[PDB]
Amino acid sequence: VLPNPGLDARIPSLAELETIEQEEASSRPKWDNKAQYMLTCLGFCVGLGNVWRFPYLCQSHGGGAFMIPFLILLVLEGIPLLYLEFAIGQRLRRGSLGVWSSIHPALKGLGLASMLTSFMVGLYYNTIISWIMWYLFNSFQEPLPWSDCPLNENQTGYVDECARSSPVDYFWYRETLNISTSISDSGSIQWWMLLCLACAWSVLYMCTIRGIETTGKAVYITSTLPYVVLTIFLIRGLTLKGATNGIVFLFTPNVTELAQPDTWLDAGAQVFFSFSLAFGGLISFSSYNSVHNNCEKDSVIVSIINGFTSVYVAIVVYSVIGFRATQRYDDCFSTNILTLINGFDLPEGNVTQENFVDMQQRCNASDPAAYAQLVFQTCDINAFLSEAVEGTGLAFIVFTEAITKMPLSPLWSVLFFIMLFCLGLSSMFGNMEGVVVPLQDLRVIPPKWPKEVLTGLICLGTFLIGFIFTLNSGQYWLSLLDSYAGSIPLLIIAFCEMFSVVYVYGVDRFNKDIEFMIGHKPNIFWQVTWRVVSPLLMLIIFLFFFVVEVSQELTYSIWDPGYEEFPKSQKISYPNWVYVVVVIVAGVPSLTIPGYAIYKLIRNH
Amino acid sequence: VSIWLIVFGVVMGVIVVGIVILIFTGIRDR
Image (cartoon, rainbow over all chains, first blue to last red; front, side):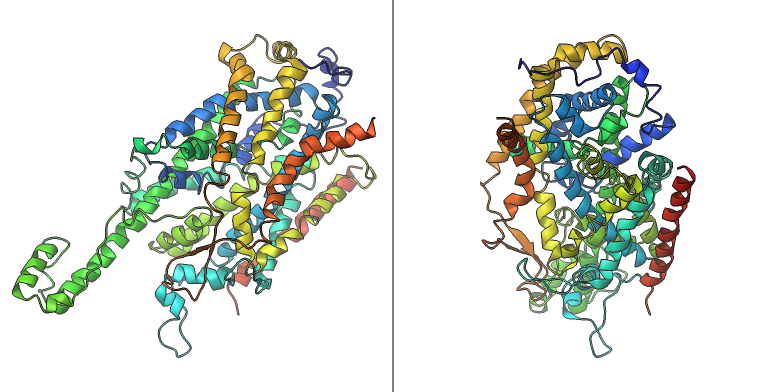
């Protein structure tokens, strides 16, 4: 629709590209195997919120009714853009920031915005990834350290916060890290945890020192292991009988929790996040294979599994959630089995989780006086399934408890954490690719000191900012990022693809591209959704952002080791000096889309 | 002294040598 003066003469125009095939190997890397290409795309998409936020959002939207707004946005918006993602990087055969230069050169705020989101999410994930290794260092041993309480100072029973709450948590607010109360007070620096952060930066830098070459040989193992070990953990769940309890909690269809506005919203944010989008490394990934490679069914293949395996990941955790809730359901009851015979004294054989309550009626009938002194702790499954956690606690203060309900409890403590390490590490590649592909499109730096020297400039450049997360206050900074950083601005970066291909590039100009790559135009629903449907849905959920922008006041949790009714959290708001930086972390990636064009308009006027 | 620094001590030695192995390959492929 737009004229674009100078639209062409920057693209390779469909008739010389067959000749560039036989000269690309001397200038650019290549996928040296068919099998090594599939290992890259699955590992960047999966995990890290599909494992902790997506199964949590099951039981906050209705368990057995959660799939319906969830599964559709696979087959309405994911399967367009990923097939669109494959088709242009194989067309232009060039980096992502170069793409929005070859289309309307008053653009290229977009290639920055892909880099300005990919660099921060690559930062604070490695903070989480370091704690995966930290608890893995704390593995290997007979009495796992979170299992027991530290004593008091008198060689007797335990300290107060390990008495008032479980030993799995206490080892988190002093052990994992020393904790602060608020976000406004920075405490200890956690210097040994800073060493654990430091080594986490290096196994990345070891593996992508030569970009496609070193990663292409180091993807054959890290992209198969996080799916196998998760297969025996499923039978481990049916080994310890604790399944069919959170499993039936996964099958609770709440039709009342479907017409909510945030039901479509929270489903829409995760399906955009379950795939790893708006980074541009996949443009370079689809530039390193053959030109006539079928990516149409490859768009069907890899999009299906990551939406299908994540459901199967949600099965294994609720078996554990059902397992932890199972034994805790009777622990208070066995205490009350003890508390019944405490004051009212039945023989220990003729008491069980049975007519216990009926014999309690005979106890109250024989005497009400001592019956008014025996307190009983009422318990219920869905009073033990009704507690939950999101973000971090599922593997750190929830999963490690049922780890300690195993006969080989230090051994499965090891096997849990290499799986989640390589899970984030495989997802730590395209955000790493999202910062180097616009970097090769900068070219104001000296072009000497080749890529291995440039590789050392990335890992030590972003080494520095993770230091504030090692503070006692540093965990409260991390709660900002999963909530705000990359929640809203991920959408409209993807929306600028829709305006470019239809009204600037021309969908019919894209139509002659697809008969070149594979041949004949695909099924007609492909051509429908690029016109209308993906432009429709992306702004409805963006409209739902303004519904949840300010309709609930911003509040973050504080721990307070000296808390009033201590075994619960405390939710306080932020100070006014904290409000000045919350717009910086999520807003400045969105400012560059008009922002460079204003600099470009005063540069060319 | 510490058990978590024992398992930390072996993985910090793995990290130092693999980066210079690929340095020798890139210098042999100049």
